[PDB]
Length: 100
Length: 101
Image (cartoon, rainbow over all chains, first blue to last red; front, side):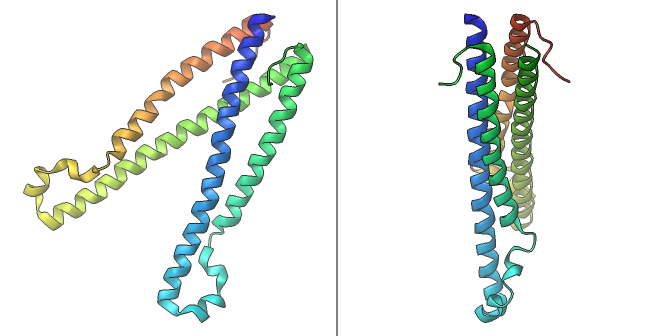
């Protein structure tokens, strides 16, 4: 039991590190999307003036990268919930302390 | 133990998917870096002439994004090895067939 427990603890540590990366990348993806829209709003300001840009706000993110990024963050939140439940069930079935 | 096997199978799928995304992301980083340098080089050729560029080739990637990207991608090999060995051991210890293509 001792050996399998250590293999499982290593597997869990690996998954947590992958998850942290997934979350960090989703956060960066949202930042990048917002920066990109900020940049386009600035360029559209130079091309058409601020009033015009105010009455065509949807054009600063034509491909809706911001909303897509928000869905990405939602999935990260979902990933966390799935992982927590899965390892908890694994701990219960093995009788091993794997996570904490 | 039928339930545990399913939980472990799922865990393995999740890990393999993470691994592939990370590898794909590093591959994308390399592609992007090469692209960036190839673009700068073309621009420099027309601005300064081919003779000049042929004597200042390192200026196409001043921050070495290409070498940096290559270095990170190279780790994929060790990451694969570590994963295969760990799960092989888990399979042996549990007596379960867990791994996937």
